[PDB]
Image 1 (cartoon, rainbow, N blue to C red):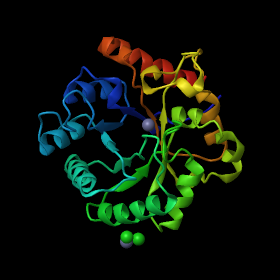
Image 2: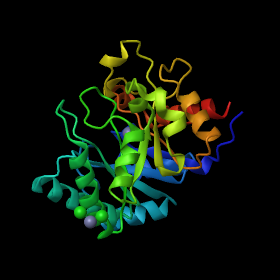
Image 3: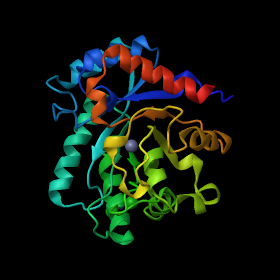
Image 4: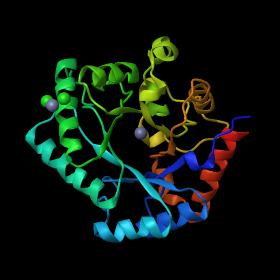
Length: 272
Ligand SMILES: [Cl-]
Ligand SMILES: [Cl-]
Ligand SMILES: [Zn+2]
Ligand SMILES: [Zn+2]
């Protein structure tokens, strides 16, 4: 059916909360992928756990992996001087491990952030990121309490900011933005989508009520239409990276074998 080069798949570290960085990298190489994402919200609380930057670089190189992003700055949108320090720390982390991009997430507490303020934040962060030679990925969050839910509108703000940043399209967040399908096909710029985050939800609770805890991997029981969201991207010309990003606490109970199975099962579902 769909011909997606295996090379284009990326494994986000959220899938493996119980694995050290070397165990995680070794698994991804065993599965013959060459892309990962690291994160500052693992149990360790550190992008590199207790390792230094050099150790992490050597590991990535030992297992032939590109670290594609770090997740994530929050809230990029409410750029106080604490948030700037928190971002500078993450920019060092990205530069040090050899990460290409750092992910930016909008305020998500039910409070309005005006588009003028978001644009100003993108401008300031674009200048700051350039200083570390890191790419920025703006990820809209679909929650009703999110200050920035539309990928289309996010792309517009980036243009107004004159920024090289791109949008991170997350299929869960698209699914929760329930006004999303109206504009999408006509208004989205595929070339300005820098990464895609995939995960499935089988949970049949109302879409309004869905949270990250329901986000598992891709099955036939998936409620969010990932196959169709991916098929559309392919048809509209997307040649970028698909990264698997589950969040559920069910993940912690998975062995290294079970993790390998779910990544294989998810990939196979897309190529069927
Ligand atoms: Cl600027
Ligand atoms: Cl500026
Ligand atoms: Zn500027
Ligand atoms: Zn995501």
